[PDB]
Length: 119
Length: 139
Image (cartoon, rainbow over all chains, first blue to last red):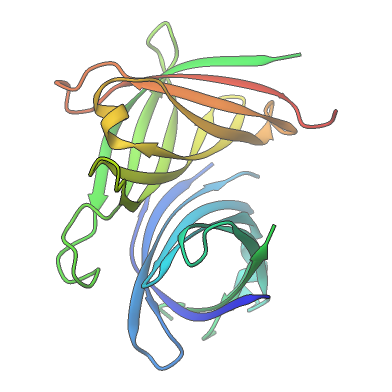
């Protein structure tokens, strides 16, 4: 049985070291625009190919996600797929995908779709 | 066949959640950080960036259990590391074991462990010794 979560996330903070690297924070909203959690993440630009590892906190548990994105695909508003794994609460033990894209081609909020199930 | 890397890492920047961010909880629930990475001869050779989330308090103790995901950039490649730790163990200067895998360069294709310990709590950069041991994922 799949667990499915649709989110909207907006960046509130980003630090960079200008192989650029970054850390960031996002507000997480449900589809009704209600504020329900937070994402923290880090990024390293491998070759432009970026590699992300992040953690998402939701009212009922926590998830880690990770993956590799081409910068230009993000900017074309293509769907990016990260792998993810529940780390606590309702998501514990579950694995799946976090598929997301820039919602609006400015502040660049994203829509993200998480699907997890037993491993 | 085993690749071993020994580092010292020291925090240079940290941010934690602010009041009002996380409903019902104060700063401390989540963090991002940066560290300077040094070799065993003490030369500055790279950077680590990371994030932390509190999972829960251990009902058997009251101790905080946290989860970390981080990335380390070295002159010859990059590694991703992640894991859960009990903060009691960390502050007691026990050795903490995280999983890690290479993401580029010399470490591409490699998997193993990142075992670390705080070298000093007095030093507000909380220097750690980290020992990474990696082997080929391909059997």
